[PDB]
Image (tube, rainbow over all chains, first blue to last red; front, side):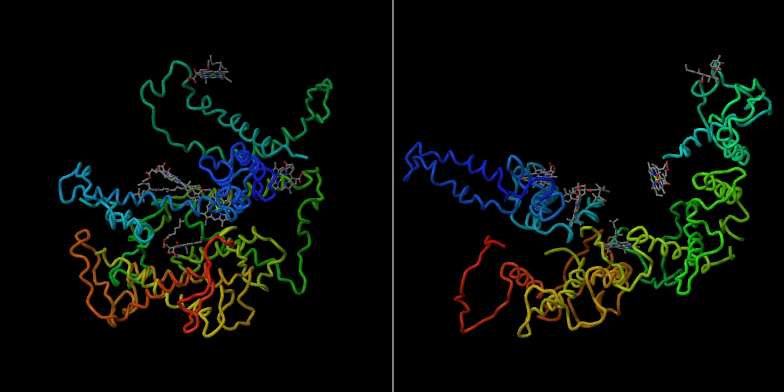
Length: 154
Length: 95
Length: 175
Length: 165
Ligand SMILES: CC1=C(/C=C/C(C)=C/C=C\C(C)=C/C=C/C=C(C)/C=C/C=C(C)/C=C/C2=C(C)CCCC2(C)C)C(C)(C)CCC1
């Protein structure tokens, strides 16, 4: 409800330009609609869509003039998450690749002699080398801030 | 609805600070000099300053700023002009 | 340093040179390492603005306030004239009291020895913890509530009939 | 294995706050009966009181909390700690943190500390499996039943995600 941008439910545009945009693919009477492939340009799909119409709805995004999702989190109201509730994971999903990324490498001086010892990967991964990826920060993310860094290692 | 002060007090406040200083003690610091010809910075030298050049004239300095502004400035424009004519044309305290 | 490592309020035990073997603050650094204008001033201040404040009575009898007591100051003076001065109000009265004050602790300027601290050795109530050591709790005692005195200045520091305000705000405003 | 006697207490602390944590909503736990997602508070109460919201039960009872917890922290740090249950040892006889302050930089070892029975420890973690049952339902299926000879292992119904909420 903030800055504009209305929650979709007053429908004005979006919902209609929608029930327009998608719905002249629908005028695909211009073929023969029964069973097809070769055609189904009409009947289905709209299932994902129109039979997801008033569905999408539904949490607002306060989709806005034009009548489309102006997608915003910034840390106000329910939204504090339309990208943050799915905004952290990414952080999470990446830099523990860094762990594998690190400990894969930080092995590539152990057992001794290295590099292409980088090309032949010694199938490097599946558990703790990754499956620590699971559990890094605020329990041990300060794998950073002691003996591994510094750095302090040799 | 504004007293034009604070500022216009401080536009004078340190004006009055370098009419200031230094009648007698030869010719008003040092010495004099520096002028043209150039004696100072990156001809060579270029160093190395203190600052206790304050402390002298301060106790003095306060008086003159923060009342003549009420005898000069916001102190009439004064009689006097006399002399006389009278007087400059003699003036309304303008107003 | 930062934490979770630190920092020896956990006794010593304790003090403590000897003892039992300790440190603890790190044997006497200085966030100025030399040192003042702003330091120990954080102290004798608010001891003695805050006594000046006891003065607003709780009143259950009536008070207020004197004979001349300035009429919120704006125009009960002087009535002059002589003449005639300011209005009064504005910069002029607000000019006298100033540089009058402005000279009193600035002749103090000249200071170096007699006596600069302990400094190397000795070989204001003299040695005084108490009378001075309050210096702290007499500052923030004050802000402590002038925070609300710039928060919700409702009407009269009746303070608690309700709770401990504690409102709570939340740390945000929100969360 | 994994690592060194780093946190014990941290997670111990956790397991301490744990059982009586899962004792908390363990009132909704229903002696026999009285549950749901909660609002109230032990029994009674009726002073003046413990209140809302220009008050909150929060900041009052949980500012002062801070010095009650920092004492431990700095207590850990500079040991510091009883004589000695929690950091660490006197009686009798838990799972040993075992080590002393340093390694070869770190490893002159690191973990020969297993051995025994069922024992003391356990229940500390029990309540976090409790939790990962007990949290998951309560907004997914917000009541807790157990029901034999009736229709356990039969069911009855269905209930998924998108309904709505
Ligand atoms: C508090 C505050 C804030 C902040 C701000 C800022 C911006 C500041 C600055 C600050 C600082 C002082 C900073 C620094 C930082 C640092 C860093 C450093 C970052 C990061 C990082 C990285 C780079 C990482 C890496 C890694 C890790 C660590 C983990 C994962 C993996 C890897 C290894 C990759 C806010 C916003 C809230 C506002 C108010 C106040």
